[PDB]
Length: 330
Image (cartoon, rainbow, N blue to C red):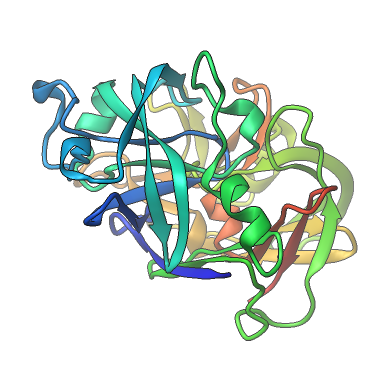
C-alpha cells in the first residue's frame, strides 16, 4: 500500500504545516501537524476542557463506531518549546492520504497548554519519530508509520515541504519526479528516539564550505533551523545590522536587508537554503526589526534541522531495519 497527502502552511510565514487526517467511522477529518520530532498522535477532542478549545476541530469518539477506549491508558507530553498536553487514549481507524491503519492509538486531549489553544489551525499532532518516545502509559503505543510499515510497498515516508506553498507527505514510495539530481543517503542514530544524523558542514552565501560534523535531528515539527552558536554567528555576521536580542529571544535583523543563502552538507552533497527562507518577518506588527530563521541551539541541547532546512529539500525517512535519511535538491 501507499498514501499521499498534501500538507499546507498554517500562515504566511510557514510557522507550521497541517495535513488532513481521517479518524473514525464515519470519518472525522482533523488537520494535524506531522512531527518527525515526536511520537504521539494526539487530538483536540470532545474531552478537552472547554475553555481550552478555541476554533479547533475536535474528535468525538462516541460518534465513531470503530473507536474503543484503551482501558487504563493515559498520556502526557511536553515539547521543546514549553508546550504540553495530556489525556486518555482510544484506538480507532486512521487514514492519511488513502493509507489506512486500524487499531491506531488516538490520544484524546483532556488538557492542552495555552499555545495549542491559541492556534486554531492545528487540531493535534501526528508523531513520526521512533515509537520508543511515545508517552502512553502503562503500555507504550506505536506511531502511525510503525503500524503501517509492514503493509507499505517500501518502509519509507517522504517530506516535501513547500516555501510559502503546499507540499506533500508520501508513505510507502519515493516520487522520483519530486526532486532533481540524486538522493544522498546518510546514517541515522535512533539512540535518542529521533531521526538523528550528522551534517558534513556548511557555507554562508557564496562563501567557502566549512567541513565540520554537525549532529542534529530532522524535525518537521520545529519551524526554524537551530545550529551551534559559532555557525549561527557566522551566518548573521553577513547581514548588516543583525544582532542577537536577549529581549526578543534570538537573532533579529533589519527588515530592509537581503539575506544570504545557507548551505548544509549531506555527505558530499549540498542543500542550499535560499535567503528568503530565513526571513520570519517583523517581530511585532509594524516593526522594522525582523526575526531570523537560523537561531542558536545553545540552550536546547541538540541541533534541529527544522522546516527552514527541510523545506529546501526532498527528504526520505527510510524506516528499514537500519534506518537512514535521504536528502535531494528540488
